[PDB]
Image: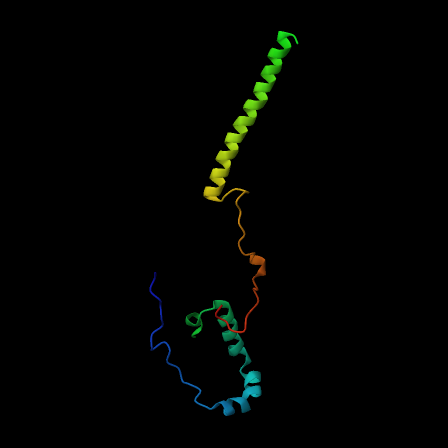
Amino acid sequence: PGIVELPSLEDLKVQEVKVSSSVLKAAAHHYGAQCDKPNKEFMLCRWEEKDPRRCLE
Amino acid sequence: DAPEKNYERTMAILQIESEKAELRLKELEVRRLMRAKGDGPWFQYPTIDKALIDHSPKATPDN
């Protein structure tokens, strides 16, 4: 069959959220309030495209 | 019986039995084709009903 098309290592570079899970859980409710819109854009794109490669940006 | 009566009764018998024979030959050929190709109303063995599929958004996206 066909060749699988993977994005490059440069296309996967991003500034990571390098905090622990307790930091995330402590900030979680205000993070779900304040960062609502790009999160829901991403999860809508992620459930509609059904492909992580189409959801990178 | 008159010979006319037996004669034309024989013709009615021959027409009925020849039509039944032609229908039996066509029935054999139809059964052969429908078993071979599967495109007729006969030999329709079941597949899974697609109405059983859940099309809701699942817990994970990639599905």
